[PDB]
Image (cartoon, rainbow over the protein chains, first blue to last red):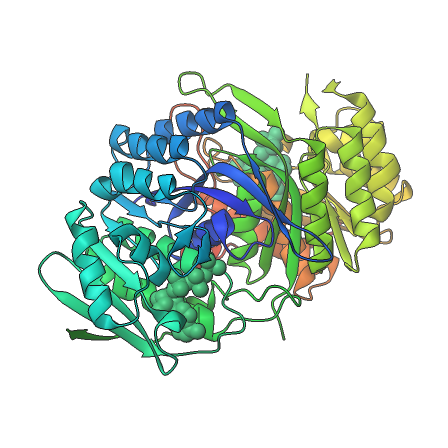
Length: 276
Length: 273
Ligand SMILES: Nc1ncnc2c1ncn2[C@@H]1O[C@H](COP(=O)(O)OP(=O)(O)CP(=O)(O)O)[C@@H](O)[C@H]1O
Ligand SMILES: Nc1ncnc2c1ncn2[C@@H]1O[C@H](COP(=O)(O)OP(=O)(O)CP(=O)(O)O)[C@@H](O)[C@H]1O
């Protein structure tokens, strides 16, 4: 009955709602032994909240990986990874480990309807991460990028994107719709290569949702590590994060985090599952 | 009302049992909003477990502090701070903040210490701002100038001296270092000495015990416990984590930070001495 060891490869969100902070918090909430290999530190200007991303040098990244690999993770999550070099190493680290689960959160920086800073990072994710992924967890924008379809606007568009992403090698795909899709219920689309499942909760408040995405992928990872099937794990993750969102709060004018502990301390949220 | 915002100023322990990892995990267990300003990254050799400390640039340290100060912590903990500059900055961020609680874990590196100047810096910059200072038995001897402490009476003398150097509340941990049948710590508020006692648990897998104790103290303060109640509750919390420590490899094993809530509570005896 030893704690499962869960590693995230991610950066530091100094505001502590997303990034590796959300990951370690979530892993802790879900009774796993959380670990991080840090890639970068993100800080925010006191006056304007402008973000500054400081990459960490590859040598300290590699030293962290050595320690983490030695410990031996049971599951690995990737968060926002800054370079193709790190994207490639993240996949290699998973294959070198005895970890049984790989959750890829394919985080991208969005510049427009259909635009990212460097599409090479998307290509690298496709090449190096998707074919190793137990679960890939794009948001609606990211799913359009990974599938090459551009803007997705419907469940039907999500089904098409999920097919394409699955076919790039991810064993399981969850495309999150959420606020980006509809304002009345929060829809995500899960696909296992055989059946498309719509996942639903109510739409909750949209003001304070910082860290929702990271938390979702973190929870998926921990639930896999603790023995839930991929389908079970993403359902449970959606519930976990829905409670966190419902219980989000205002930290300052710029950030309102999800309450990562809300599932366990406040309330559970039921997820409706329907074949579509 | 809202979750209390608790900041730790500490390095990353890649093995994830101590350092900022223990802090954030403990803060989360105790229903606070944990934050970190990272000072350094510590890694371990896969074959010997020898530590390698990589400092973070001061400018990234400073930019993290600016973000955290803007958010406005309710409580701040200091973990192992490697330089006089960082020690001084830590005290300054607390005084600039509207935080009501400052918990100083006066971590020293045994050689005698590496960096005796850092002991002097902690005394100058941190002790007079500390709500609670949490030296282990070695550190208490260093802070007090008494040298090696080996009894509750020695701890009483050290706590008096440390209080007189400006710390509002002092908890000197005895624990396995004091090496008695039970695990004793000593709390002092300038008026009364309280001995805190638990069972002495296995000693092999105790990595992160010190960090976890200070982190728990900080979260308990932030959530409304008095300093005395906070250190009693922290000892119970860490005692369960220690009881439930586990083997990571042939060189280390961490405490189970979640044990108090997931597994069991541990009783703390409180007596005036
Ligand atoms: N306001 C809201 N109400 C209910 N569910 C929501 C919601 N906003 C998002 N969701 C759900 O939260 C999960 C995460 O969705 P998404 O990937 O869009 O997170 P995010 O980008 O808003 C946060 P971050 O980037 O700060 O870590 C999905 O399950 C989605 O359906
Ligand atoms: N094996 C054990 N059984 C019970 N209590 C213990 C213990 N080891 C430490 N403690 C307690 O754990 C807390 C932290 O103690 P302390 O800071 O002395 O850590 P430590 O024993 O790790 C010294 P170091 O950091 O040098 O390894 C204190 O409350 C102390 O009493």
